[PDB]
Image (cartoon, rainbow, N blue to C red):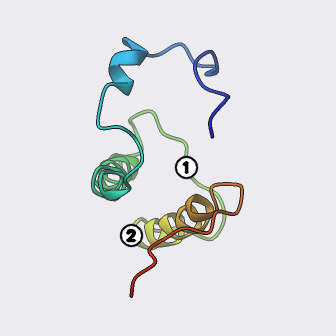
């Protein structure tokens, strides 16, 4: 279920949104974890450097990897619940 999507992004920065959306039919997390993880790594990597458009410093998380674990964690639970409870993960045998 998705109703809010399209004209909703207060930030002038996007080259051919549709194109940016042009990819494997969103659904599988395989690319989410793969890509996501990769990106994250990048972000953090860059985050390290002070000078380079960045302003991340709050709480007792004076770390990267660690902060990464806690982040991915909250993101995991949050994602899993996707805001609204959704019983569906992997009904294995």
Which quarter of the picture shows residue 20?
top left
Q: Quadrant of the C terminus?
A: bottom left
- Which x, y percent locates residue 7? 62, 15
Name the outermost residue toward the front.
93
Q: CA distance from mark 2 to mark 1?
A: 14 Å
- Which x, y percent locates residue 28? 37, 53
Give the residue at x 39% y 69%: 65
The residue where tag 2 is placed is 65
Give the residue at x 42% y 17%: 17
Q: Nearer the viewer, residue 47 or 88?
A: 88
Q: Secondary structure at mark 2?
A: helix
Q: Secondary structure at mark 1?
A: loop
Q: Nearer the viewer, residue 59 or 32?
A: 32
Q: Nearer the viewer, residue 47 or 79?
A: 79
Give the residue at x 67% y 29%: 3
Q: Quadrant of the N terminus?
A: top right
Is the residue 52 above or below the residue 17 in the image? below
The residue where tag 1 is placed is 56
- Which x, y percent locates residue 63? 46, 68
Give the residue at x 40% y 82%: 92
Q: Are marks 2 and 1 in contact (CB under 8 Å)?
A: no
Is the residue 66 above or below the residue 16 in the image? below
Please identify, in this view, whether the residue under mark 2 or under mark 1 is nearer the observer.
Answer: 2
Is the residue 35 above or below the residue 8 in the image? below
Q: Is residue 46 left or right of residue 73?
A: left
**Residue count near mark 1 (Cα–Cα under 10 Å), binned few <14, some 14–19, many ≥20:** few
Q: Is residue 34 left or right of residue 32?
A: left
- Which x, y percent locates residue 2? 62, 35
**Residue count near mark 2 (Cα–Cα under 10 Å), binned few <14, some 14–19, many ≥20:** few
Name the outermost residue toward the bottom.
93
């Amino acid at each position: 279920m998705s109703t809010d999507t399209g004209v909703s992004l207060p930030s002038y920065e996007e080259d051919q949104g549709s194109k940016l959306i042009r990819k494997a039919k969103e659904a599988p997390f395989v690319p989410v974890g793969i890509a996501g993880f990769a990106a994250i790594v990048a972000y953090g990597l860059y985050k390290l450097k002070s000078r380079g458009n960045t302003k991340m410093s709050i709480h007792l998380i004076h770390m990267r990897v660690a902060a990464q674990g806690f982040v991915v964690g909250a993101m995991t639970v949050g994602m899993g619940y996707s805001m609204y409870r959704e019983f569906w993960a992997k009904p294995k045998p």
